[PDB]
Length: 200
Length: 201
Ligand SMILES: [Mg+2]
Ligand SMILES: [Mg+2]
Image (cartoon, rainbow over all chains, first blue to last red; front, side, top):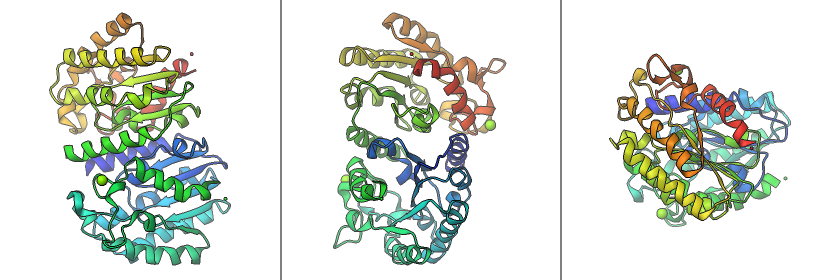
């Protein structure tokens, strides 16, 4: 909306005022990143939120500078579900994620970059139909995102296999109250999956 | 619309239920104006924690005190009411509900220092959140009563409003906002400057 536009500039202007240091562990993405208290979840003061609700691949791309100038230890990226909601193809989304990977590697070569599987979605709550109705695209993106990681020599994290239900290909509803965002237990699963990579 | 705000509240609330609160913790508690900051970064203080929920109202804050107060935090910083203003709620009923937050906090964690922060001015200039912005006058009505309440209950009143407002208009200085309601980074630096002395008492 005009709200997501305005919220973007609020969060982006704030991040411009906060220093990133070489010890930092950045979580970078859309609402699913924005929704967490990352330092609390890992109990690690070097872990920082660079999530913006409604963010898309090129929104993340356009605000790398206040993050990369700090040369953080780690970036955990989760992006693309909002690009799905706009009818963008997995291939187009992969090309944009490529720009982010290559920009990070060039501006901050020492940063460990971890590409996180797009999370599954679920239309069972009848919300975010632009997202939940393109549930098949989640798999499409990750089947390309993993080889993108191998080619660019960066880690791929499979969150998807944990959050997904075997026989639907949709978000386990115990992780979500809308089919898109995580409840507490959703972030506790994330924590258990990614924790070993926060402590590499 | 209100469904996304309702589900977002349960999302933030259930996460806070999994996040332990301790005797050293400094809590920023309130609505999207609290939610929007990275508090521990703003104050370079690992003890400072975000319990902001976009869209929250006084009774939404009241109903979620348990997982904050049971850890007996060092400080709570409260900023709440503008979403109640947006529902046509009177400054009197708002104060009434803020008074129940204050007594629950004292009762459950009496060593917790509580700080009551002036409700921030709004500005209809951007034509956004017209529920909030048309009612810019109700801001100062709440604050006229909020300072005497603090004094009554023996808790701090922090005046943010006098720094954010344009005295000529009675509205949010557009330099701190792109929508009439929420803060730009600059907005949060002005907030830090005002509150850091209370954060470090
Ligand atoms: Mg559920
Ligand atoms: Mg402005």
